[PDB]
Image (tube, coloured by chain):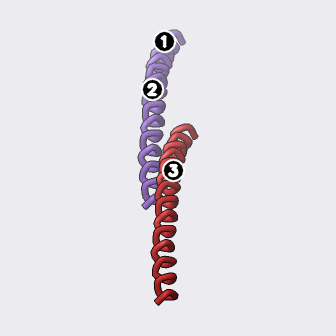
Chain colours: A red, B purple
Amino acid sequence: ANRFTSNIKGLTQAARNANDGISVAQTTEGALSEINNNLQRVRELTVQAT
Amino acid sequence: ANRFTSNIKGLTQAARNANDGISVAQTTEGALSEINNNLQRVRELTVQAT
């Protein structure tokens, strides 16, 4: 039972740690999406300029 | 989808650029027409003068 309790607490903490990676990836992906929009507008401008 | 959006924006801007060539050709054609009329009158004058 002591080993089982240790495992249960460890796995719960592991899931909590896992959620952090999801948060980081979401924020980073939003930033990259904004960069992508800027790049798209830059490409449109180059097409207009050439 | 990102590639598709880039391509659509590029093609729309390409058509927008294309219209400018039509405008240039129209203006130049008008100028050439006026030059042609003046040349025609010059030819008539030479026929009268010879």
Q: Is residue B19 above or below residue A11?
A: above
Instruction: Indicate the position of residue A27 as horizontal and vertical percent values.
Output: 49, 54
Task: Calculate the distance from the C-alpha at mark 3 to the C-alpha at mark 1.
Answer: 74 Å
Figure check: A15 above or below A44: below
Q: Which residue is mark 2?
A: B27
Residue farthest bottom in this picture = A1
Q: Amino acid at mark 1?
A: Leu
* Depth order, front residue of A49/B20: A49
* Occupied quadrant, residue B16: top left
Q: Which mark is residue A37?
A: none
Residue at point 55% right, 37% down?
A: A49
Q: Residue at x 46, y 41 (%)?
A: B18
SS state under label 2: helix
Q: Is residue B21 above or below residue A8?
A: above
Residue at mark 3: chain: A
Relative height, residue B21 to residue A25 (above, below): above
Q: CA distance from mark 1 to mark 2?
A: 28 Å
Q: Nearer the viewer, residue B33 or A16?
A: A16
Of labels 3 and 1, the one closer to you: 3
Which residue, given by chain and number where applicable, does mark 1 sit on? B45
x, y percentage for residue B37?
A: 44, 19
Q: Secondary structure at mark 1?
A: helix
Residue at mark 3 to residue at mark 2: CA–CA distance: 47 Å
Q: What amino acid is found at the position of numbered circle 3 in the picture?
A: Ala
Q: Nearer the viewer, residue B32 or B44?
A: B32
Where, quadrant-wise, is the C terminus of chain B in this rendering?
top right
